[PDB]
Length: 14
Image 1 (cartoon, one colour):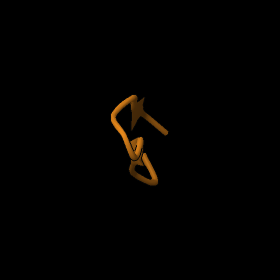
Image 2 (cartoon, rainbow, N blue to C red; image 1 turned 180 degrees about the vertical axis):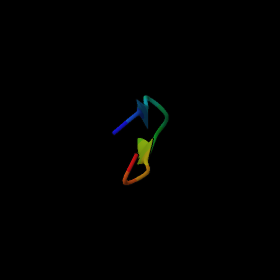
Image 3 (cartoon, helix red, strand yellow; image 1 turned 60 degrees about the horizontal axis):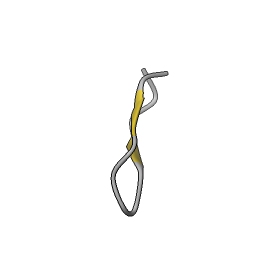
Image 4 (cartoon, rainbow, N blue to C red; image 1 turned 135 degrees about the horizontal axis):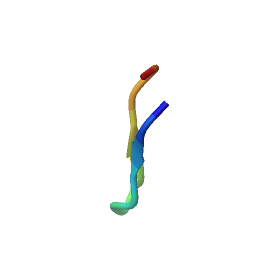
């Protein structure tokens, strides 16, 4: 559920 605002934004199924 927690996504990191990177580029590309890395998000995990958390």
